[PDB]
């Protein structure tokens, strides 16, 4: 198990997905045209996980870029690292999806999906041992949300034994394109609960607050939020992209993180938060990554309990000190980790730090406090749905009110299920 | 692509198309003959201005539009006026005899003589389009052509183009400039027969515009030329999201998602600022906070109603010019604490913002000042139902005695249509009341 196939869908999907390929291409010594001008052999040892080798020792991202309009994807080709992506993997429609889940899932996107699956199958075939798929998308618009979840469903049909990962950007009124976002998100969460093994919940609420409160950006752009997203994505893929004892794969992650199959919504965290000169001591990384202020999902982990945790330290540091500090927070806050999964915190260290920082920590948590996120979206949803507001946009593409009711019910069930283990 | 076809019906529609298209030409640097120096791609292109203008091989940029009237006098002035070369003669369409302030003649008698010709020409523009977005229909409520031909056209357009989006800019009648006693009948008939076929409808109240011209521009007795120049500015602010590139530019359809919570509730209130004379704008730069604040002054509205005595369902701000998000957010924060803004309990209270960098322009020899920045607010308030109510009362006064009804019945209509239309407006008034009531 090595090769992953990456798909990015919609405005958000392709914006954050572009930053991901920018960040990791720098980490693996690949340049804006595709050539390797590195220095360490550790950079190329598992370059195969995310890149294909090409004619002339070029490395080509195993990346499929999907949108229902060409706006965002002409920007990706324009932008700093655009010329690296394989041009056949740009698969785009013309009319877009108007922030409408139904258009993504049932009408506009249905027209386009079979072409995306031909590129998926192309990349899937020239793979020694495919472990799975990761998708970047938001849940709030129509393409990345509705079409994205349509893809997932199709990929599962054709490759029912491979892993499915999402980086799924959850919406907030604090960073809001349209009033129908809670609808779109609730329709997609219903899909994600059934058809993914792992989902990283990137809440835009949490990114806005990190940007505002902790980084002193008064007027935060999507660029400022995506700076935080690509550093988190860099962190939660480190163990796949580098060595050397942890034979870490997506299946192993799924097995150890997910005690119950529907409860696979991970809260990510990063330390230190940036946009420095003083490197952080291991105690500080350990305090910071576990801090609510450093979570990429707007949930207080003190309101819930940690089912499982996976922590990843980057830089040159004492592993003695890393165990000591990781054991200190467990022993000093033991009520917040479930007694009925012994040794639920697993920690790893990797010598290569990220660009900029001498040392950093990335956190992956399956906390029951994630319910707060689904409760927040369940509330915004009901505010509108109890008066059937804005529904005509969805019923005009053939959807029924019963489908909204179903979806509202699955999410509220998810919330009940997370609440069940907080009290056990 | 994303092409938008404008259809201008009757005198008000036609004369407002002049104002608009004259304005768009100045906005994009298109000369009267149709040439555009700054366009290097000759014969065609994908540029944002191409949503409103096709290119010919000779370098002519040509409005994606059709002017239609049942008498030649108003369109003859486009055929011989400054911009006569801009339009292909087949875009400018006339009959010999008008509807005579009668919805019936505009819809049935004079109207059905020219309707196939109009759809045939609309079709010729629709086939120059690689991805047609929809139509923009400019017409008066009160005229016979504006009311009855438009209704017929809208019906027919729903047949030929399915659910392809249709926006109206509708001129709502006012006593200061009104031409006919029967305008309330025409208004209620067109409103009724158009309501299933229009996706969004910006009403413009001639009185509101008349008052703004007197008050803010110091114009003693405004003509139509005065009003249309102001209207074209508002129309331009709304269509500017379709005509310009921009990092912070939110498309108009995205605003529509927010503006229309149920099919029948599709009447946004517009409010524009600043409307100011050159005399008053000299040494008087108006900041983002001042023009934003001016959007919640109901004297700056396009329809005379009071949003303060009603409830909001959406609030969109379309800024153009020297504007950046920081200033906008600060301005909105100030307004939230200091002004009368109550949303319904089923809407989120966030204001949706869009920004075009191209600053607004002015037509040579006009009354508006050239300003560095400007803003159009589109709100969906229950207050706009006040406008339906005033007009519905005028209709009821006359309809109770059957005044003028014989002129409509003689051209083939029945009393059934009148009461069927009035009950639809009764229901619409009741809908705008229901949405405002809190949930349980
Ligand atoms: N704002 C504005 N209103 C106008 C203009 N011309 C006419 N009106 C108004 O429109 C209404 C009358 O309708 P018109 O558009 O003149 O009538 P028509 O559609 O040509 O119909 P007939 O002439 O009866 O066939 C009245 O309320 C007028 O004040 C104009 O250029 N601008
Ligand atoms: N963090 C982040 N959120 C985004 C970005 N672009 C859009 N969004 C959010 O994504 C949602 C809208 O989805 P979008 O991707 O534009 O729609 P789609 O293209 O139709 O899938 C809203 O919640 C936006 O705030 C981005 O670059 N970064
Ligand atoms: C109870 O928690 C876990 C147990 C096993 C695994 C499997 N592999 C893995 C991972 C890991 C796996 C896939 C992708 C990204 C990753 O960062 N990160 C760690 C850190 C420490 C460690 F011991 C294993 N890790 C994951 C979590
Ligand atoms: Ca289609
Ligand atoms: Ca061109
Ligand atoms: Mg968007
Ligand atoms: Mg006329």
Image: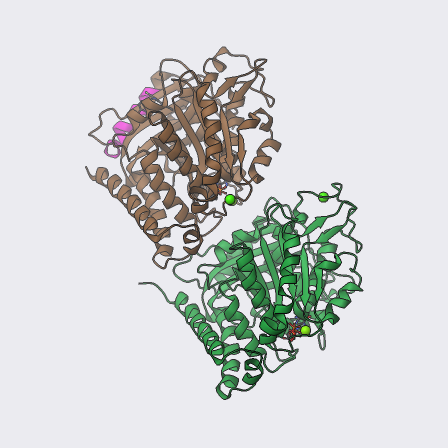
Chain colours: A brown, B green
User: Residue B213, can we see it?
Assistant: yes
Displayed quadrant of residue A190: top left
Task: Look at the image and tell me in which quarter the N terminus of chain A lies.
Answer: top left
Task: Identify which residue, A309 or B354, lies in the foreground.
Answer: B354
Give above or below for B129 relative to A89. below
Residue B65, percent across and down? 67, 57
Q: Give the range drawn in magenta.
A: A322-337
* B39 or A420, nearer to the observer: B39
Provide residue B177's location: percent of width, then percent of height: 66, 78
Query: Is A329 colored magenta in this rendering?
Result: yes
- Does B47 lie within the magenta span? no
x, y (%) of residue B256? 52, 55
Q: Is residue A137 left or right of residue B77?
A: left
Viewed as shown, does residue A199 lie left or right of A306?
Answer: right
Total numbered labels? 0
Which residue sits furthest bottom?
B401
Residue B425 horizontal side relative to residue B142, left or right: left
Task: Give A320 or B422, whichever is nearer the viewer.
Answer: B422
Does the magenta stretch mainly form a helix, a strand or a loop?
helix
In percent of width and height, residue A213 lies at: 46, 42
User: Which of these two is toward me, A326 or A41?
Assistant: A41
Which residue is drawn at the image coordinates 49% and 14% (left, top)?
A44
Q: Is residue B211 above or below residue B333?
A: below
Quarter of the image for residue A78 reads top right
* B86 over B170 or under it: above or below: above
Q: In which quarter of the image is residue A94?
A: top right
Is B53 placed above or below A266 here? below
Q: Image quadrant for the C terminus of chain A?
A: top left
């Amino acid at each position: 198990m090595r090769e992953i196939v990456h798909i990015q869908a919609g405005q958000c999907g392709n914006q954050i997905g572009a930053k991901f390929w920018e960040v990791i291409s720098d980490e693996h010594g690949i340049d804006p045209t595709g050539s390797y001008h590195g220095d360490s052999d550790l950079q190329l040892e598992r370059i195969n996980v995310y890149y294909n080798e090409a004619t002339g020792n070029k490395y080509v991202p195993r990346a499929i870029l999907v949108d229902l309009e060409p706006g965002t994807m002409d920007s990706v080709r324009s932008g700093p690292f655009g010329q690296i992506f394989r041009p056949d993997n740009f698969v785009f429609g013309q009319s877009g999806a108007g922030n409408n889940w139904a258009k993504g899932h049932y009408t506009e996107g249905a027209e386009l999906v079979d072409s995306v699956l031909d590129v998926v199958r192309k990349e899937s075939e020239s793979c020694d041992c495919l472990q799975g798929f990761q998708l970047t998308h938001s849940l709030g618009g129509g393409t990345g949300s509705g079409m994205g979840t349509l893809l997932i469903s199709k990929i599962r049909e054709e490759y029912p034994d491979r892993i499915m990962n999402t980086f799924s950007v959850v919406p907030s009124p604090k960073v809001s394109d349209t009033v129908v976002e809670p609808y779109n998100a609730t329709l997609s969460v219903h899909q994600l609960v059934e058809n993914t093994d792992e989902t990283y919940c990137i809440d835009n609420e949490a990114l806005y607050d990190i940007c505002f409160r902790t980084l002193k950006l008064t007027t935060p752009t999507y660029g400022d939020l995506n700076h935080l997203v690509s550093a988190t994505m860099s962190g939660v893929t480190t163990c796949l992209r580098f060595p050397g004892q942890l034979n870490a794969d997506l299946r192993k992650l799924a097995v150890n993180m997910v005690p119950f199959p529907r409860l696979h919504f991970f809260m990510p965290g990063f330390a230190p938060l940036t946009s420095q000169y003083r490197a952080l001591t291991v105690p500080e990384l350990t305090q910071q990554m576990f801090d609510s202020k450093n979570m990429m999902a707007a949930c207080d982990p003190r309101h819930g309990r940690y089912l499982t945790v996976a922590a990843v330290f980057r830089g040159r540091m004492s592993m003695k000190e890393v165990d000591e500090q990781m054991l200190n927070v467990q022993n000093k806050n033991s009520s917040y980790f479930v007694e009925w999964i012994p040794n639920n915190v697993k920690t790893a260290v990797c010598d290569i730090p990220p660009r900029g920082l001498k040392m950093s920590a990335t956190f992956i948590g399956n906390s029951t406090a994630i319910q707060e996120l689904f409760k927040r979206i369940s509330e915004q949803f009901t505010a509108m749905f109890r008066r059937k507001a804005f529904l005509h946009w969805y019923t005009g593409e053939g959807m029924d009110e019963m489908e909204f009711t179903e979806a509202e019910s699955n999410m509220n069930d998810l919330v009940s299920e997370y609440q069940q283990y907080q009290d056990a | 692509m994303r092409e938008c076809i404008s259809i201008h019906v009757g005198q008000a529609g036609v004369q407002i198309g002049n104002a608009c298209w004259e304005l768009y030409c100045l906005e994009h640097g298109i000369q009267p003959d149709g040439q555009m120096p700054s366009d290097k791609t000759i014969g065609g292109g994908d540029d944002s201005f191409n949503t409103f203008f096709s290119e010919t091989g000779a370098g002519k940029h040509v409005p994606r539009a059709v002017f239609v009237d049942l008498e030649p006098t108003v369109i003859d002035e486009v055929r011989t006026g400054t911009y006569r070369q801009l339009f292909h003669p087949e875009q400018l369409i006339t009959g010999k005899e008008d509807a005579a302030n009668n919805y019936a003649r505009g819809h049935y008698t004079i109207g059905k003589e020219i309707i196939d010709l109009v759809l045939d020409r609309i079709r010729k523009l629709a086939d120059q389009c690689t991805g047609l977005q929809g139509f923009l229909v400019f017409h008066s409520f009160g005229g016979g052509t504006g009311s009855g031909f438009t209704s017929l056209l809208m019906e027919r357009l729903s047949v030929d183009y399915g659910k392809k989006s249709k926006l109206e800019f509708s001129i709502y009648p006012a006593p200061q400039v009104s031409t006919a006693v029967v305008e309330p009948y025409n208004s209620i008939l067109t409103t009724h027969t158009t309501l299933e076929h229009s996706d969004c409808a910006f009403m413009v109240d001639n009185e509101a515009i008349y008052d703004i011209c007197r008050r803010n521009l110091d114009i003693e007795r405004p003509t139509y030329t005065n009003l249309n120049r102001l209207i074209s500015q508002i129309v331009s602010s709304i269509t500017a999201s379709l005509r310009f590139d921009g990092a912070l530019n939110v498309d108009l359809t995205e605003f529509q998602t927010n503006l229309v919570p149920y099919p029948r509730i599709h009447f946004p209130l517009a409010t524009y600022a600043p409307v100011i004379s050159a005399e008053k704008a000299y040494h008087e730069q108006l900041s983002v906070a001042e023009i934003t604040n001016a959007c919640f002054e109901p004297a700056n509205q396009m329809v005379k109603c009071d949003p303060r005595h009603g409830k909001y369902m959406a609030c969109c701000l379309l800024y153009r010019g020297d504007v950046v998000p920081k200033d906008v957010n600060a301005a909105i924060a100030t307004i939230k604490t200091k002004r009368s803004i109550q949303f319904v309990d089923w809407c989120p209270t966030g204001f949706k913002v869009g920004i075009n960098y191209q600053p607004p322009t002015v037509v040579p020899g006009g009354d508006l000042a050239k300003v560095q920045r400007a803003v159009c607010m589109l709100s969906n308030t229950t207050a706009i139902a006040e406008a339906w109510a005033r007009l519905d009362h005028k209709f009821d006064l006359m309809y109770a005695k059957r005044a003028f009804v014989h002129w409509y019945v003689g051209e083939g209509m029945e009393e059934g249509e009148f009461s069927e239309a009035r009950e639809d407006m009764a229901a619409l008034e009741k809908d705008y009341e229901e949405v405002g009531v809190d949930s349980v």
